[PDB]
Length: 179
Length: 89
Ligand SMILES: CCCCCCCCCCC(CCCCCCCCCC)(CO[C@H]1O[C@@H](CO)[C@H](O[C@@H]2O[C@@H](CO)[C@H](O)[C@@H](O)[C@@H]2O)[C@@H](O)[C@@H]1O)CO[C@H]1O[C@@H](CO)[C@H](O[C@@H]2O[C@@H](CO)[C@H](O)[C@@H](O)[C@@H]2O)[C@@H](O)[C@H]1O
Image (cartoon, rainbow over all chains, first blue to last red; front, side, top):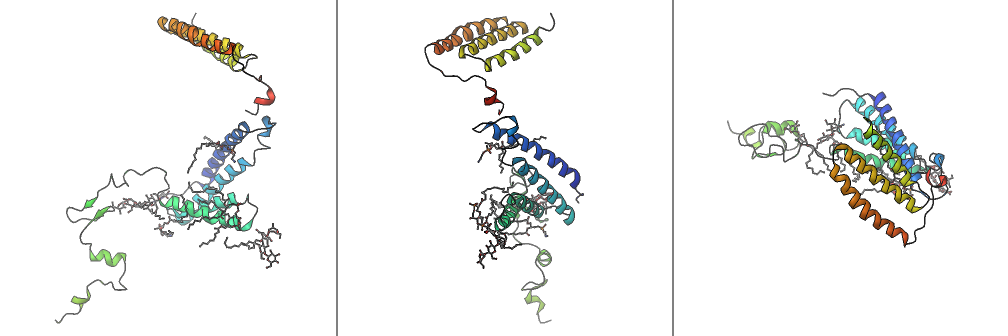
């Protein structure tokens, strides 16, 4: 199944990596600049960069692990909620309410589309079509993903779709026959 | 005479710091020639006596000569290592 997340310590680890990334990026902006700049203008003329890094890190991993622990399953919806929280933190530097809402919903939609494709930049190996069973089944078996058959079982049709609209467990013809 | 390699390692560090912080552009280039000599010392030290003289012949005797020859008859401005310039780095 799944096992519950360490929201405490993953959020501490995320705050550590965000602090380090803010240190590195503030040093990078210091070195790549003009004007009178010294060693302690790294945190005064930084442009608020450590706040960006740490706030995004705490917000995303807190909301991700909390949503995965509240829903008790793991899919791309947790990436949607965590990206909504990250967009909230990135949109609060904009001191404006409609832009804040735009940052929230659009970053959450982009991160949910990210987390729905697998939440991986790279590939999954066995989930690929190259490294999976493909083509026809050669004789009758549970049809996997990436596989094609000629006929499907009708019990699978009734269980997956339903028993409602035009769909029935026995066809209309043989349900109405003379004997 | 055990710590010879350690000594060449340390002296090479010190020579690079004197390369990147030097008044005059050719004071910096003479420190580079000294670093070539420290290299050839390390190469004889490890067991490659052939290569050390190949370094002294090719790198010192041709590349450094070309480099010094360039610095002589061309004009190159230089700021020196101000602390105002480089502790932002
Ligand atoms: C604008 C339109 C946007 C459209 C985007 C759609 C993208 C949706 C992707 C769907 C899809 C790729 C299919 C894509 C094919 C072509 C796509 C066309 C281009 C799309 C660009 C990626 O499936 C991903 O779905 C994610 C959630 O949906 C998961 O997230 C993560 O969740 C948690 C992980 O454990 C993490 O804990 C959490 O961190 C993550 O978040 C991912 O793990 C998962 O890989 C499904 O592929 C996969 O499906 C499965 C289940 O059938 C297949 O199962 C196998 O086969 C059967 C017997 O063998 C069995 O039944 C089945 O049991 C067996 O395992 C696989 O073979 C595989 O192929």
